[PDB]
Image (cartoon, rainbow, N blue to C red):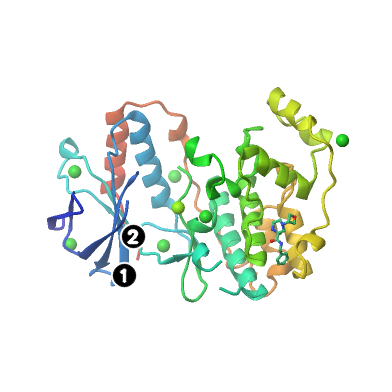
């Protein structure tokens, strides 16, 4: 057990191992974050103190979920866990959880500058490489958007902030909804990992044009922007929408054909246009997958099928389990004390 030291930073008490130095507050509903220098590894790191991690069954399960997911992710294009600690010496006094990751500077917003087509190729390639890994473990990110993509000086990219959002957060003219697939925006059906590919299409379009693809002022305005581009659904997709009310609403709209994407994305690489047509498909069954997209000719200069790894299997059976707060807390404690740091 390392030696811990205490200090008060912006009205909260932080108790952390001596290896973490020069703590400086950076941000704050799920917890507070400080930047620090890790004297053991030489990295600049982000230290997150969870706020009220075991206040309810829902909150305790969410704490366990986040720790399990972060401990599993080991990929160049996905955020990983450098450390996790608690100052508690036993389960009986266990109350606080701290998570440590590489400190990230800019996100794709702070670049979306002047992007060449070669820049778009490299950025989208890295997102898809990370997504092939995530999806191979049957994990769905569910919240991909430019603010959840970190980029460094050399245009190297990491996916962060997995979906672990409320009604107010998704209301109105808000970027929190502009990248969401329509079947999850409107609860049409049970969704799957194809929702993340819709988000990648929205992001790629924005990198090519400098503009949000579907900046709707509310759910219905956004749906109208989507259907004007990709066309209204045919009977085949309509059969798959489980809400009779949502089906009824869609059929009240006048039918529209899919637009010509070469006349929307004027002057773009024809191979980029082709890939966008394969991502932005209304029927999620028919979208290109991450593994298929990596083999698309648009990425010819970066694709290497010997260097696009998959994940170890991931057991999510806890998600259907019903437990008491203290049982979720004990499972979290075991995962804290069994953590093994990366090489
Ligand atoms: C895609 C779009 C755009 O940003 N167009 C500008 C552009 C800039 C560079 C290269 C090509 C195109 C167009 N609007 C209208 C709606 O249907 C076309 C929808 C969203 N933004
Ligand atoms: Cl230490
Ligand atoms: Cl990382
Ligand atoms: Cl504690
Ligand atoms: Cl964003
Ligand atoms: Cl019609
Ligand atoms: Cl597992
Ligand atoms: Mg975020």
Q: Nearer the viewer, residue 333 or 165?
A: 165
Q: Nearer the viewer, residue 127 or 206?
A: 206
Horizontal and vertical percent position of residue 243: 68, 25
Q: Residue at x 47, y 41 (%)?
A: 315
Q: Residue furthest top?
A: 244
Q: Say if disc 1 is inside 8 Å of ligand 3.
A: no
Q: Say if disc 2 is inside 8 Å of ligand 3.
A: yes
Q: Nearer the viewer, residue 257 or 193?
A: 257
Badge 2 or badge 1: first in the primary sequence: 1
Q: Which residue is mark 2?
A: 82
Q: Residue at x 79, y 59 (%)?
A: 261
Q: Which residue is mark 1?
A: 43
Q: Are marks 2 and 1 in contact (CB under 8 Å)?
A: yes
Horizontal and vertical percent position of residue 294: 66, 62
Horizontally, residue 234 falls left or right of residue 38, namely: right
Q: Residue at x 35, y 66 (%)?
A: 343
Q: Residue at x 36, y 27 (%)?
A: 323
């Amino acid at each position: 057990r390392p030696t811990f030291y205490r200090q008060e930073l912006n009205k909260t008490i932080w108790e952390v191992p001596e290896r973490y130095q020069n703590l400086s507050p950076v941000g704050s509903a799920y917890g507070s974050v400080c930047a620090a220098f890790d004297t053991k590894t030489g990295h600049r790191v982000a230290v997150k103190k969870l706020s009220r991690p075991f206040q309810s069954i829902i909150h305790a399960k969410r704490t366990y979920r986040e720790l399990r997911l972060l401990k599993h992710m080991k990929h160049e294009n996905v955020i990983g866990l450098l450390d996790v600690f608690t100052p508690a010496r036993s389960l009986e006094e266990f109350n606080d959880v701290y998570l440590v990751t590489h400190l990230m500077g800019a996100d794709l917003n702070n670049i979306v500058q002047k992007l060449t087509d070669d820049h778009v190729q490299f950025l989208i390639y890295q997102i898809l490489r990370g997504l092939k890994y995530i999806h191979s473990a049957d994990i769905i990110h569910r919240d991909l958007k430019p603010s959840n993509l970190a980029v460094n000086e050399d245009c190297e990219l990491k996916i962060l902030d997995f979906g672990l959002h409320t009604d107010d957060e998704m209301t109105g003219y808000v970027a929190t909804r502009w990248y969401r697939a329509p079947e999850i925006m409107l609860n049409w059906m049970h969704y799957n990992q194809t929702v993340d590919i819709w988000s990648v299409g929205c992001i790629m379009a924005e990198l090519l044009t400098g503009r949000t693809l579907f900046p709707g002022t509310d759910h219905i305005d956004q749906l109208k922007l989507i259907l004007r581009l990709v066309g209204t659904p045919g009977a085949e997709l309509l059969k798959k929408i489980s809400s009779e009310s949502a089906r009824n609403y869609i059929q009240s709209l006048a039918q529209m054909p899919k637009m010509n994407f070469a006349n929307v994305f004027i002057g773009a690489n024809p191979l980029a246009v082709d890939l966008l047509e394969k991502m932005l498909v209304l029927d999620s069954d028919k979208r290109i997958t991450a593994a298929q997209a990596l083999a698309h000719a648009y990425f010819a200069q970066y694709h290497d099928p010997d260097d696009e790894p998959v994940a170890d299997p991931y057991d999510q059976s806890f998600e259907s389990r019903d437990l008491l707060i203290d049982e979720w807390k004990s499972l979290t404690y075991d995962e804290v004390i069994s953590f093994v740091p990366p090489p």
